[PDB]
Amino acid sequence: GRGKATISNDGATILKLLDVVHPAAKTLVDIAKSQDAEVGDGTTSVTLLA
Amino acid sequence: LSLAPVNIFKAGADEERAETARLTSFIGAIAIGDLVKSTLGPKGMDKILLSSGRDASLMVTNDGATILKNIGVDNPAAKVLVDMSRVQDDEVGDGTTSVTVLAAELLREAESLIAKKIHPQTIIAGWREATKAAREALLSSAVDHGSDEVKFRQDLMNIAGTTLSSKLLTHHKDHFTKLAVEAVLRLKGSGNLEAIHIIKKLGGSLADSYLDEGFLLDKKIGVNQPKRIENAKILIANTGMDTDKIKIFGSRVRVDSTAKVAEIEHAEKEKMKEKVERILKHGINCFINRQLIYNYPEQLFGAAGVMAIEHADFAGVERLALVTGGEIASTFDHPELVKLGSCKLIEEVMIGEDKLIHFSGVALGEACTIVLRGATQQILDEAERSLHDALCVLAQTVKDSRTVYGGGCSEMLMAHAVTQLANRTPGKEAVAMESYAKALRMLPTIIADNAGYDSADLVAQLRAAHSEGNTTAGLDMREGTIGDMAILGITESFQVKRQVLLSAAEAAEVILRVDNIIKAAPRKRVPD
Amino acid sequence: IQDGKGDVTITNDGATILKQMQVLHPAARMLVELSKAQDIEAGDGTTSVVIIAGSLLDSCTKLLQKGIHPTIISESFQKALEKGIEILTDMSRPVELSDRETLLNSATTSLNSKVVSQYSSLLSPMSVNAVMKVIDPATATSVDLRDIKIVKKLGGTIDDCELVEGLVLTQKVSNSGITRVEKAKIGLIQFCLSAPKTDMDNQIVVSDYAQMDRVLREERAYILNLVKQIKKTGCNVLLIQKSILRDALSDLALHFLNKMKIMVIKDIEREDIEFICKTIGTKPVAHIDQFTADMLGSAELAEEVNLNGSGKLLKITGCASPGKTVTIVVRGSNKLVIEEAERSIHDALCVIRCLVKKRALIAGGGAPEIELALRLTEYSRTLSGMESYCVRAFADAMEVIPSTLAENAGLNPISTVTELRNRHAQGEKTAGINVRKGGISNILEELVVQPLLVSVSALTLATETVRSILKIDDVVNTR
Amino acid sequence: GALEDSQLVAGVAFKKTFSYAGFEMQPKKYHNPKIALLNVELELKAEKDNAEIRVHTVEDYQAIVDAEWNILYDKLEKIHHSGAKVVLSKLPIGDVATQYFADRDMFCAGRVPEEDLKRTMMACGGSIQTSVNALSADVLGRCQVFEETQIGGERYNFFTGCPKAKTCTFILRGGAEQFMEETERSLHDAIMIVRRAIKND
Amino acid sequence: SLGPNGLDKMMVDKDGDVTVTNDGATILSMMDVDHQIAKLMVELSKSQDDEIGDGTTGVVVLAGALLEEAEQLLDRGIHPIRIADGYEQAARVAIEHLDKISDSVLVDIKDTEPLIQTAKTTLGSKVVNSCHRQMAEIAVNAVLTVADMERRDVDFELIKVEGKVGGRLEDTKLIKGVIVDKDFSHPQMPKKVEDAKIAILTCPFEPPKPKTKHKLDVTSVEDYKALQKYEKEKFEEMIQQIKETGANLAICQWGFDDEANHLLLQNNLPAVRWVGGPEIELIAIATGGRIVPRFSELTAEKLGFAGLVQEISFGTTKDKMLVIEQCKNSRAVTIFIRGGNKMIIEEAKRSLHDALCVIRNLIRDNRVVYGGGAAEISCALAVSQEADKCPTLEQYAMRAFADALEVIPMALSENSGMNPIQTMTEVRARQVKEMNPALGIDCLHKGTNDMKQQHVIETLIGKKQQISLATQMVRMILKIDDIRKPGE
Amino acid sequence: LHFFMTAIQELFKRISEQFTAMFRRKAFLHWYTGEGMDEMEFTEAESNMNDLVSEYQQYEEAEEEA
Ligand SMILES: Nc1ncnc2c1ncn2[C@@H]1O[C@H](COP(=O)(O)OP(=O)(O)O)[C@@H](O)[C@H]1O
Ligand SMILES: Nc1ncnc2c1ncn2[C@@H]1O[C@H](COP(=O)(O)OP(=O)(O)O)[C@@H](O)[C@H]1O
Ligand SMILES: Nc1ncnc2c1ncn2[C@@H]1O[C@H](COP(=O)(O)OP(=O)(O)O)[C@@H](O)[C@H]1O
Ligand SMILES: [Mg+2]
Ligand SMILES: [Mg+2]
Ligand SMILES: [Mg+2]
Ligand SMILES: [Mg+2]
């Protein structure tokens, strides 16, 4: 909302930058943070698989 | 169809491309030089400036430096000519009107050259060879003096009577020329123009002004202290007589009885008595301080017959050390390493409705005061402003004593040197050089246009007389004919004319190179 | 005039009306500063100088339509001004300062135009008396009006105004009961009488019950010590200067001072110490060891007066060593009458000041204005060119004042100036407008005169302003 | 810079911090220094915020003023006797201490972040000292080179040459603010992949 | 705004200010944009000035022309990653070719002339061209003085740039000391000295005061009289300590007193009051003295040496300045800029900073190439010749790189007044036929296209960065496909 | 003497001016006395209120003989 641009190719930071408010869709954003906390890679491969 | 389909700038920001930026920079600069042109020459008129938010301060002026500093312009290219005009006033103090008109006539001749499909870099490169050939022909025409006293004094009188011409002081030119040339010779070669204090006050005519032989102070003496003392010995000091010396530490009194407080209070009162007695060991009768003097030491000076002057700022203490000849003293421990002032009579004078302390008979006299009298408040302000232009230009002639014949002779001189150069260089620069020589010849045109004379005939006579040998011919504004400049006595300063060409050629170069004006979003003002 | 804050002032001075107005034209804001200058040096004629300046600038409208450059008018006006001085100087008559009949006649002429024209058989003599008591008539070059103090007091009427040859104080005494002292010894003090305070931050520490009683006891013996030094000198009236950082007089010092029959007067300002020292001749005292019986100024009577209910006042009269100061008390019924009565007296002091600087007397009542309008008419016939039109314009503009004096009195202005000018070129040159008889007669038989400095200073300043207006050609608005 | 100009150092590297007058009068290259990792304010101040002095005579007034100048000079002398050449401190370093170390060819630094002093310790082998009363040979650091070079209009301090170093530092050279953030996030993925690949081959 | 015949831009500040400049870094800095891609180009030029200092308007022209050439390739069905892959291969051919035609001459103190000719070209573009021979001698002489020759670095804090409006543009000179805008404390002090030993002090001249919450108790009259005596002996003890050591001038950071001001005057010992922080350490390096925090530490071995300390005066204003020169070997120098305009001084300061940054680069790397477009024509032939042996859908990307690389010659010719395609074609035809890679565009109309004879010199690392940095920004733009932003 | 926010003297001066004017006419007094108060309770309020003003210190036609 201020004007700062965040340019990135990784799922984890893309889903953190969207103001998702849908209760069902918020499960897919929570499993991405789990993957980047345990292994750190494969974040966007668990979003298409889910 | 619009300025590119995508949006790059923000909301409120504007851009101007080549064809429209040259339109703004060229109409902005000409507008500045048209308002100011009316105040040029011996017969120039006068303007009125009213403030709309500054409590309606009405000021009336003639010089082209205070007018530009007051007019609020929002044109980007008109702000360059207002800045360069301030630097001229702060450098030599004279020639602000001529530097803006010349730099505004160069731009007017550079718009018809772009319409001839000439690249701007061609004009600039052609003008550089025109300024170089113009400053060489002015240096060679300067008359260096200063080896004779009877000749140098006559050169300073001619300069002073030439600057005061367009100004309101031109009515009494025979009287204000002697006050302006004698006040500069009092400085004895020191360029400190601050030493001349101009005191202005209402009442009386403009012809009642004079230059005092001694000095004048707008201060007061203590109570029941002698008004006059003949053959005074002044001591100039800067020391704290306020209450007492606070003796800066973190100290305090912690006695346990109220009689012990009374003993300490009596200790302060005997601290100031000792300080006063150390002053009197110098053998003085006129103590002058730059801070306040309280009621205890005021009576100590009045019991021994000493005049005490209190609350005189730095402007009145530094000046008094150059007039009488003393020194600013403190710590009062060695009376033999200090030097006292001297006078012959000190009295109280009545100028209008106020009292001033008069210093008649002085040792050195390196600073002075000028008393200006007038009918209105705007005449006093304009007399002070005009007189400051006479003192500033006479402080430059003493350091660099070489003069150049003025009154239109110098402008036609440099214009002929460019013409002979423009008839030699092939290419397009011959066209650009003629524009430079065309802009120098309109300065004498404006002077004759304000007087209602046939300008188109006088310039032709001057140009024909400057290409055959007569290098001193110029305008004669008292009759309307052509007269010699070495006989009538129209003389200028070499540094003033040199700073006009160099400043008016740089500002026309910076402005001409611009081809894109980019404006940011203005800062908004909160209405409530 | 009614201010926008709710202040109403009934005035007649030309320098006061133009100050209270709020004009916005720049060409008229310069007329206010013109009348200010005349009030500073001359002190009278502030209304005449605006009429002259407002009539000369008008005569310039027709000359511009005839094709005359404004520069020529500026130089041609100086020609008619330098000649006008030479016509006023030989008209005047020298006067001495030992002739009360001349000063009395000149102090009423600038008194009969105001609201106190009826009360001039009393204000004129007390105005001449107030100036001869300040300057030395043997060697006088200027008079200071700062040596005359005007006191405004409400109640009563104008004819109750008097001249006090002493000191008048507007504040009552602090001591109660003692209001009448004869053969007093006045003394000025600049130090305070309270608990001891030093410039450094001090404090008293008590750590025992026996020291509590000593603080009160030793304090009481300190104030008593200073009071016993004052009574040793034989003082009756006390004058304390105002102090703000510390108390100047405690309740204990006042209790001791009443028991010794001494009048105490507090709250004296720091700006009027000089006027007090110049009146009773009192050495100021700023330290207790310097309070000697020579630092005192004697007097005859020093008692407070009580009005009809408008307040109290202090009068000290019969000073053993009088100075060169005098004071005036102004009495009126309304706040508006007092202000106009005060400005009228200040006008009668500036006329006496003008006589000592330039001892020359010139007949008034429109006599000089018509004389410059007659010599300049024949003067312009000798000249040739475009300057012969500007001098004729100068002469015609000088008939406005002789026209105004006859128009306000209900006479025919055309017949009065025609009769006045005709009689001015066939004989005597002291003929003016007689407002009492109703025609034109010799103006010296009406005993009306005016100083020469007023008529000249109202002309030199007028021509200079017009010469500056003609220089202006453009008006631009700034920030 | 360019993406191929990124370097990996074998020690620590941190930005130049605020410096007072005299910082340009001391050497900026050492051969075998002795790092003194400290946590102290070496500046002229009050001993304790909760303090008060009640002197009676002017002779004791002058001795107090000389007592504060002797407390500070006692700490600086203890550092100089230990043979140290580079000193670092979280708390600020005053200008008096800066000119003390300039006259003895000794480097000084202050207001170092906590994350940078801890990275030095496991690269040189010292320990953070809150007091100067014990500066032995076993509480000092050591390296092989120390200098202060310029990279991209910035001053950086280097501590290369540590055979027993157990930490590194990445210097990333790009051309925009978002070029470096995307390079740091991309490097953060190979770090965790290799870290997980050692526990599970 | 490119080349010697370029034109500059007017800039108006948000509040009320006006700036005239030709530098590419500052133009994109004060221009307020809203497009996100436009903010990437601003950072592209800013990262160039701080690294080198010259070429900041040349990178954005090449990057903009590098993106335009890829517009046709995308329309033919070409993946953007394939374009961004072929671009990097070309940038490895041009950089490896730039070292082959690079010539290194020498860098030292005794023969300085190639250094002068290097700074002459960069100053050729800016408004300072009337006196650009003189301003090319200040830039070179003020770098080898402050630069070390072993560590090969330059400390720009040691070079002070101070401009004062009023006067003439050619009055700019290089001072070999420190010029501070202050004056002597007492009006009756001598304005000049001929042999001064500088006494640098940090501590003020007031009586001492401890930092802790001291309180001094006065419980008698003799304690009070012993306090006045304490104060007056402390002042006299200070002047004795300065005079004893042989000092001639006193320099103080904090202020004096009413009493400590006369004692300096009465003892013929002038002083300067309230000088700044950074200026003090420049006088210490220049004069060779040391800074003392107390009077007890003031010895004879901690004093500076000046040859002349004067107080120059400007025109009819009250501006006084103290100058310090005629010193021995120094590591601090100042540049005094004059001029009759507000905008001249600011642009003169920017142009001088570019000249200094060019010489600093030559210390790190001696080798240079020849400008005027010569490097681009040569680099565009090496890429195009190598693209003929790459049959994998990369010849299109390589050929597009060599076509956007020739926009620099086509920008100089268009600005000069010549025909781009008519002059550029004739230069490549002459360069291939001969073996002379130093042929450029005759922008100044001198007759010869040979840049070696015309003395046009460009630093190598300046040209390397304009290609390596410009290529990498194009890789971000070609990688970005989605935008998500709020609506206004 | 422990009241914080002149020297508060203005606040207590205006309150007792209205209070005295109200109590002189005994207006609206029956609302308080009828539920258990008395006249002397209000007297102690104004007598005590005057004491605090005194602690907060700021710093007829017959005068002939004594
Ligand atoms: N050399 C290669 N050839 C083909 N596919 C590859 C190659 N290297 C990696 N990949 C694939 O690319 C994917 C990388 O996805 P990535 O963007 O890294 O997702 P994340 O960021 O969530 O790890 C992996 O699933 C892998 O199967
Ligand atoms: N008496 C005179 N006769 C002819 N020319 C004059 C005379 N006095 C001044 N000038 C000319 O008028 C020009 C403008 O002077 P002025 O308007 O007074 O100040 P500025 O030089 O600032 O414009 C000068 O160049 C001078 O040559
Ligand atoms: N005398 C010259 N002749 C031909 N080309 C020049 C000359 N001087 C500079 N140039 C060219 O001008 C180009 C742009 O430089 P300039 O306009 O100074 O801005 P910047 O250096 O910031 O890009 C450079 O590539 C250089 O090759
Ligand atoms: Mg991955
Ligand atoms: Mg002039
Ligand atoms: Mg009158
Ligand atoms: Mg360049």
Image (cartoon, coloured by chain):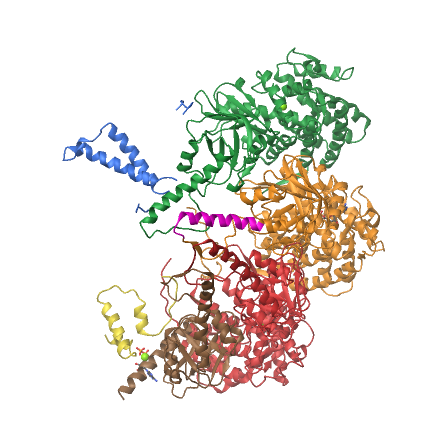
Chain colours: A yellow, B orange, C green, D brown, E red, F blue
**Does residue C383 appear to the left or right of C365 in the view shown?**
right
- Image position, residue C264 (x, y; %): 46, 32
Residue B352 appears in the figure: yes
- Image position, residue B10 (x, y; %): 45, 58
- Image position, residue F52 (x, y; %): 30, 40
Count of marks, rendered view: 0
**E26 vs C332: above or below:** below
Residue D176 appears in the figure: no
**Does residue B92 appear to the left or right of E67 in the view shown?**
right
In depth, the one of A16 and E140 nearer the eye is: E140
Residue E273 drawn in magenta: no
Residue at 71% over, 60% down: B432
**Does residue E405 appear to the left or right of B448 in the view shown?**
left
Dominant SS in magenta: helix
Range of residues picked out in magenta: B255-275
- Image position, residue B95 (x, y; %): 69, 51
Name the quadrant where ligand 4 sits: bottom left
Determine which quarter of the picture holds residue E146: bottom right
In depth, the one of B194 and E19 nearer the eye is: B194
Looking at the image, which residue sits at the far front?
C232
Determine which quarter of the picture holds residue C222: top left
